[PDB]
Amino acid sequence: ARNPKCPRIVKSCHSKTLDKYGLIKYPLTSEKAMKKIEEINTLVFMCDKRANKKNIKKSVKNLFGIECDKVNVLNTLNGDKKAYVRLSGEHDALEVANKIG
RNA sequence: AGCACAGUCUUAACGAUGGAUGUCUUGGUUCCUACAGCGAUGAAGGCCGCAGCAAAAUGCGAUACGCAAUGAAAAUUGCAGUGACUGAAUCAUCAGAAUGCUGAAUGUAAACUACACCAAUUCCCUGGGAAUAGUGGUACUCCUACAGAAAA
Ligand SMILES: [Mg+2]
Ligand SMILES: [Mg+2]
Ligand SMILES: [Mg+2]
Ligand SMILES: [Mg+2]
Ligand SMILES: [Mg+2]
Ligand SMILES: [Mg+2]
Ligand SMILES: [Mg+2]
Ligand SMILES: [Mg+2]
Ligand SMILES: [Mg+2]
């Protein structure tokens, strides 16, 4: 195995990878997204292209205290991802929507 | 209220169409003078992004029409905003910090954001306390050391 006298390259700056901010941008408030809130218990978010399904689940949980059981994804033509997030039964989508806007 | 035949051709006066002429020039062209390469510490070129409202060109790189520092030094604007009674609003300089995916492109591939193996990795206080599937390495040829094994 390698036993260098010293590493070739050493970084010392703050991390450059995407964290929870920059991985979720903002909720989408179109007239199709407002309908999902009441009769489907679903919220819609716009996300960075490089996000996974698991990434979005974790980031939404850490940002808004949201428990979810299903995420669906689609890449749009403006360079963004759209996420349809089903909220678990204990959560009511209306109160979560009111808590943030 | 009345009087000129119509067409065709000629000449004056006033207009239409068109963009010559004259004047202008932050642009070309030639000559003279000085200096001179960049790259595995990742170049030239290509793609993708960045502004409160933002298409092109110009400028920048997840700190993204700009940060820090140094010299000047009150304004900058379409609206909204931001600034002193001078590290602040703006201009210049530019040495610190930062610098996406690629490309000789170098783990294996490529009208794929496809697939491997090895080491888990990165922070904060001063041995604790946290976070994260995230980070780095692995082409070919060659030189100097070294390591053991093999033949003789
Ligand atoms: Mg699909
Ligand atoms: Mg006649
Ligand atoms: Mg040379
Ligand atoms: Mg590029
Ligand atoms: Mg000072
Ligand atoms: Mg100053
Ligand atoms: Mg490769
Ligand atoms: Mg194929
Ligand atoms: Mg060869």
Image: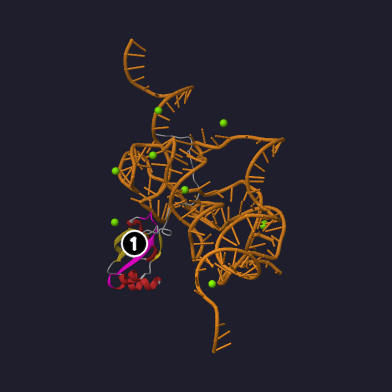
In the picture of the structure, the residue carrying the numbered disc 1 is A83
SS label for mark 1: strand
Q: Position of residue B64 (x, y in %)?
A: 52, 56
Observer able to see residue A92: no
In the foreground, B18 or A87? B18
In the foreground, A30 or A14? A30
In which quadrant of the rendered view does residue B103 lie? top left
Subunit bearing disc 1? A
Residue at 32%, 57% (x, y): give it: A53
Q: Is residue A10 above or below residue B48?
A: above
Q: Is residue B109 left or right of residue B10?
A: left
Residue at 36%, 62% (x, y): give it: A60
Q: Quadrant of the N terminus of chain A?
A: top left
Based on the picture, tell me whether residue A42 belongs to the magenta stretch: yes
In the foreground, B18 or A4? B18
Q: Position of residue B88 (x, y in %)?
A: 63, 62
Count of marks, rendered view: 1
Residue range in magenta is A39-51
Q: Is residue B18 left or right of residue A84?
A: right
Visual colour scheme: secondary structure
Looking at the rendered structure, the kind of residue marked 1 is Ala
Q: Position of residue B151 (x, y in %)?
A: 32, 13
